[PDB]
Image (cartoon, coloured by chain):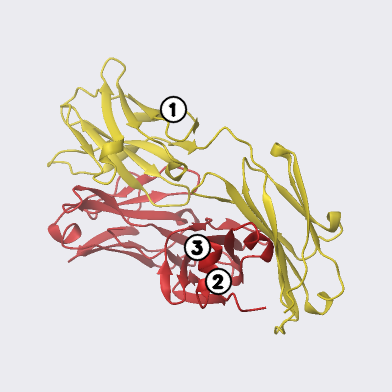
Chain colours: A yellow, B red
Amino acid sequence: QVTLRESGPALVKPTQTLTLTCTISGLSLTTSGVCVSWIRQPPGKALEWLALIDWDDDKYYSTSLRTRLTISKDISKNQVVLTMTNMDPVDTATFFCARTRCTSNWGYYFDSWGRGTRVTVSSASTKGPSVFPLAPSSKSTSGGTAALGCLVKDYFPEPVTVSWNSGALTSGVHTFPAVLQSSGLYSLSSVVTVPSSSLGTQTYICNVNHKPSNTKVDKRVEPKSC
Amino acid sequence: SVLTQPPSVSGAPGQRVTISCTGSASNIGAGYDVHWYQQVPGAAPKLLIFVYSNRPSGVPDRISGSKSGTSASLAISGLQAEDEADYYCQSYDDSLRGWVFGGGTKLTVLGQPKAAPSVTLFPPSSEELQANKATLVCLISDFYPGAVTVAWKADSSPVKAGVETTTPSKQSNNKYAASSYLSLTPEQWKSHRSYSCQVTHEGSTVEKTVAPTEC
């Protein structure tokens, strides 16, 4: 029954230093053969090994991030600490610690994992969205429909809501999940599938409400013209 | 990724699928062990296969691992609903001098008909250009299995910078949706013949294209 648990701040600001702690139970970091690694996982992306420390004070680091990382062990507390300097929003990720089999008679693999802890790198600033129309074409399609929408760009924090014609239009509406961008700001799009025959005569307005910043935007979406 | 996996593999309950892990002479070819991890969305990864083919306690024998040459492979016979998850191969690379993972494979256990994505690509709006900004918006919906890869091109040349893509999320109808955004200067948008969003769904790549002269 080896268990590992990560702890640390949920939020860190750019350029700040992140300290994460891994508490190991049921196994002594002083025992020959015991190694622990830190692994990160950006949202929706692959696992990436960052660092390893063994029962000698031997420290191994990703060659691409070595200069940003330090791995250390607090034998008093039976903890392994990761420090990562100069945090940027592109570093937002879930961090895991894992007991690593470390010796030739066993292998070199991640045997027991922590549950992970998400670290989001972001500013203290609330920011409302810029809203832009996504204009539809009147050009013929097989299905006799066209897509129009509103781009809701560069806001923070989530959530935001989008309605169409003050809630009177609900059919054909698809508001997509937001993307967390490399800037640490969010964007999303809301699109409506409408009949092409209406593009000349119906008004379409998206109503955006970003309650965290108290920003509200109405944007008329007009068909492409020439 | 130093180790290459297919983004998506899928089968119905009871079928057999395989997941390839393709490496090189600096990792799998050099004899560095290959291991596999299973990750259910929402949870941490778990060891599934160690030293090529050994299964930890609790992992069934319908899950098998093998190695040949510069590649390794994970076979899952008799798919069960609990097998739906992301799978990672892992090895060591002596050119990067570090532990390396594959890019990951989403294994879907099919519970409804496969469905190709609908893709809609919008150019920058005139209003955004008037703020001296430009975003292309690639919206991907109604696809199953819930796994896609998105790439972008300027004319015919791959564009890697300025790309932000969501992970697929479930829609009300239990198909999936995703979006990808390409940020550009107004000058780049006006300077190329066109820009394209390429959406790959289980080996099928559809491309949508927009151009600054399209009015």
- Give the total of numbered labels: 3
The answer to whether residue A147 is above or below residue B128 is below
Task: Determine the chain carrying the residue at label 2.
Answer: B
Q: What residue type is labelled 1?
A: Gly
Marks 2 and 3 sit apart, C-alpha to C-alpha, by 32 Å
Q: In which quarter of the image is residue B95?
A: bottom left
- Residues at marks 2 and 3 touching, judged by CB atoms closer than 8 Å: no
Q: Which residue is denoted by mark 1 in the rendering?
A: A8
The amino acid beneath tag 3 is Ala
- Amino acid under disc 2: Lys
Q: Which of B17 and B86 is in front in this view?
A: B86
Q: Are marks 1 and 3 in contact (CB under 8 Å)?
A: no
Label for residue B147?
Answer: 3
Please give the chain letter of the residue carrying mark 3: B
Q: Which of marks 2 and 3 is nearer the N terminus?
A: 3
x, y percentage for residue A142? 70, 85
Give the quadrant of the N terminus of chain B: bottom left
Q: Which chain contains the residue that carries disc 1? A: A
Q: Mark 2 points at which residue?
A: B190
In this view of the protein, which residue sits in the foreground, A79 or B14? A79
Considering the numbered disc 1 on the image, is that residue within a helix, a strand or a loop?
loop
Q: Is residue A217 above or below residue B205?
A: above
**Which mark lies nearer to you, 1 or 3?**
1
2 or 1: mark nearer the eye: 2
| Residue A177 visible in this rendered orientation of the protein | no
The quarter of the rendered structure image containing the C terminus of chain B is bottom right
Q: Position of residue A60 (x, y in %)?
A: 21, 37
Dots 2 and 1 on the same chain? no
